[PDB]
Image (cartoon, rainbow, N blue to C red):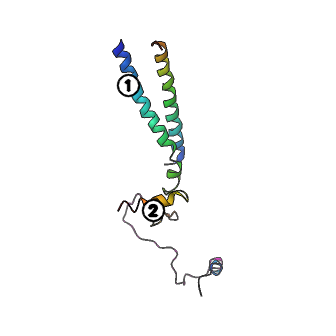
Amino acid sequence: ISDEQLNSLAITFGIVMMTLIVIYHAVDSTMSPK
Amino acid sequence: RSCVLSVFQTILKLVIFVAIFGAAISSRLFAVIKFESIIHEFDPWFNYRATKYLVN
Amino acid sequence: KGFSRLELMKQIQTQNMRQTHFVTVLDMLLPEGATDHYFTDLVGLVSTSHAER
């Protein structure tokens, strides 16, 4: 496996893990007491 | 309402841990798929010499 | 007398024969369609090897 595909797999897992945090914290901020 | 929101929190946390257990694994591996897979430096070649004694 | 490197560099520099008595390459013959070759070793993985037909 060339590390260009490993590079795209690395940033892809970074963005997919890093976007869902914000919608988790938005649901948990809007519809919860604290 | 409480069951719906609680199930949503649980499933979303499971998908979070499946992603963030994978981003680390994929970030460490440039020196293994670039080259062969061998122990790297001066100090980690005693430890490998001792856990190969215990193991047989 | 020993093993001198630069005299072997002088052999490699001016080459006219295959009449020498040490082995440098060797090639095994394979079955017809062979797919995923590798040439490892006892200390690692030697990386100077390429296939033919």
Tell me if residue C39 comes above or below residue B35 in the rendering: below
How far from the left and from the top, in percent, is residue B17?
43, 32
Identify the residue shown where x is 49% and y is 16%: A29
Q: Which residue is mark 2?
A: B49
Indicate the secondary structure of the residue bearing disc 1. Answer: helix
Tally of marks: 2
Residue C25 within the magenta-colored segment of the rendering = yes
How far from the left and from the top, in percent, is residue C53?
45, 63
Foreground pick, C49 / A21: A21
Q: Which residues are magenta?
A: C11-36
Q: Decide which of tag 2 and tag 1 comes sooner along the chain.
A: 1
Q: What is the C-alpha distance between the residues marked 2 and 1?
A: 44 Å
**Amino acid at circle 1:** Ile
How far from the left and from the top, in percent, is residue B10?
38, 24
**Amino acid at circle 2:** Arg
Does residue C37 appear anywhere in the picture? no
Q: Which residue is mark 1?
A: B11
Foreground pick, C1 / C18: C1
Tell us which disc is closer to us: 2 or 1: 2
